Image 1 (cartoon, one colour):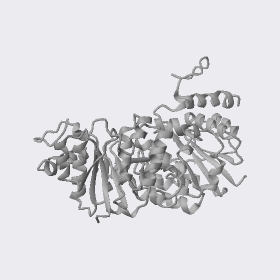
Image 2 (cartoon, each protein chain N blue to C red; image 1 turned 90 degrees about the vertical axis):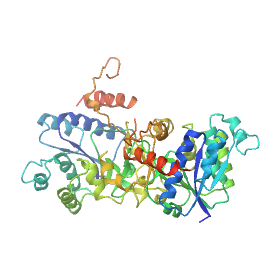
Image 3 (cartoon, one colour; image 1 turned 60 degrees about the vertical axis):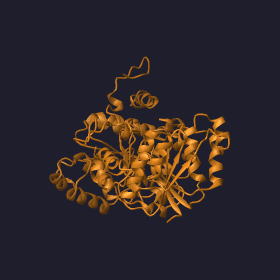
Image 4 (cartoon, chains in turn orange, green; image 1 turned 180 degrees about the vertical axis):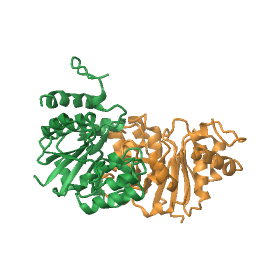
Length: 245
Length: 245
């Protein structure tokens, strides 16, 4: 299936270690789709070489470059540099449908059935459930949709300063229209109690939303612990699958 | 509209002060439906007299009495006394459709359009959004449905020990079937940040989920403060509307 792909984003070498675990977990449960990672010039050249060993395409996005399609929007909204870089996922018109996943997510089972969904399909966000969490969403690349999002960013910006705010404003009918575009919470399980004991075993994707990202923990290979099984599995994939590359 | 009603529950005099504010807020925004409160013998006789000044029906429920329909279930599940008392809302077969609201909720605008919904319509719960919050839900009373819930309580109980767990287990298709049965989050806004600045103004019902209930705060009538505008409005309705009764 060279027609569809999983898309992620790395703005530095720290988040690149998260995408390496995400891409390895996508390979571990045997995905038939392509693996795409969007990278900025802040990612070092040697870290991009490590990313090529996991992902099928390492696409460079530099919103600071005047030739970039989102550069004029950046001058109006200089605080949305990361957001405008992520919005380049709609520019990947070589694919018909994609599933974007942030670098701080981890896959626990095959989620290729997400490509049976339409744009825009996303899981509900905890805290404000009438907004979807932009950590995992199924979309369809389009130059039209991409230019629509850039104009919305220039006109209004983002009410949370990130991508989730503007994406919820653009796809504002998500909470009341089609329930098939509501992904189950197990496709984007927030790391932040009795409900977990009943449904947490059916988790497919865990979203690390804590203050300390998984790669910023101090991992002890002797005890296989850190300074909670999901955080241990992240470092297990990182040491077993990612490092020998 | 003597055919439909709002239903609440009071197990003691402390929660009875919350139902007095809830019923007063329902009267403040002019509801055309009946006001029903379920009370246990633990509510004092004089507090029931105060409840009759607000609600149209004060219905007594005593699961400790051997003649109660849920008494045999209580012997199997002695920890679900409050839950089995709340489940008596389905026994109110004199109404065709009802909207249950917990005593720790507060109404900010007319929500009579909730009776355009079907059973079971409820708002998503924050924390685990694939489960609905049982603080506000639209249901249809039925002896059949009530006996179905009692048997589920005897067989499995509740995975959270309260009503929300068993109600989510019984109405398990809520998260994936009809989106019209997904009430907007403003119909049950949890008191527990950038999303509030955009949508919080459209709030219709606020659900006080904090550790300290609104009636357990120390209210100073001089400064109109407590020991945050929703907690102030609760005590304003309590002092202006409830006390002169």
